[PDB]
Length: 304
Ligand SMILES: Nc1nc2c(ncn2[C@@H]2O[C@H](COP(=O)(O)OP(=O)(O)OP(O)(O)=S)[C@@H](O)[C@H]2O)c(=O)[nH]1
Image (tube, rainbow, N blue to C red; front, side, top):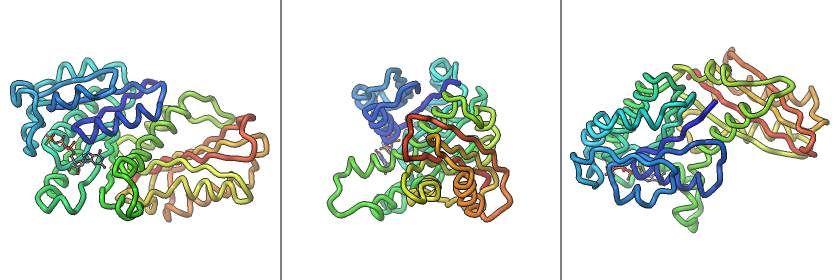
């Protein structure tokens, strides 16, 4: 199953560049922008410049109608770059001109083409003002009605989880953790055949046309290693929705040879309780003898 990560706008490409510098293998990146000046500094193995005649190589100057029309008009090259993909993550800063307008349509392209399409967008800092927060909003709703399932990140939460000293690029990286977690997690299920296996059909089942989504990976060792990992796993302070009310869950548990039944049940109960609802849970496990004292819980939860 081939996974493609698509940045749309400068935000999206920064997202991409950081994720490359982090090193993610067996995921194919695509950078997409109106701004040529940007794309020239992207590390993406594949780049697509859109709205060329609309903007002559400049960004969309905070009118999304431009990013929209731009992409809608470079559809065919986009499609060629997409093709061969089973799942696509569409990543974008909402509020700009390019992202807000083009991103909803990259994903609508991606959905019609048949891909399982996950939106991962940022809402902007309150300090960017009301007007941007509203353009951002319009984007997010287009993105919701355009994808299978959407992840939203109000940028303001960074200010809540950062200390007064943290460089800006660090805060943005911490926001990247969401995308990195989903991508690494799914990539990992797909690549490994478990004792109780999860595969891509399960991903399709919990993620197709489900609205809001949470994606986590939690890692821990110690006494309560399984409760602690499942608790790390299901908890971003960076999201718009919590886990509560979830209606679909896919959950994988990876451990060494001492992975107990009792504690697999314990992590699964962390989750099942946490939704506060009768869930459709699909459950899987992997015993990786390399792993010594630590376990990793991968959780993907939708249905809000
Ligand atoms: N969290 C995070 N947010 C970003 C980043 N880059 C931009 N943003 C936010 O996302 C929004 C849009 O990002 P940006 O890439 O500048 O828009 P654009 O679509 O490129 O807009 P334009 O070039 O046509 S004007 C901005 O309002 C900003 O708040 C980033 O690297 N990390």
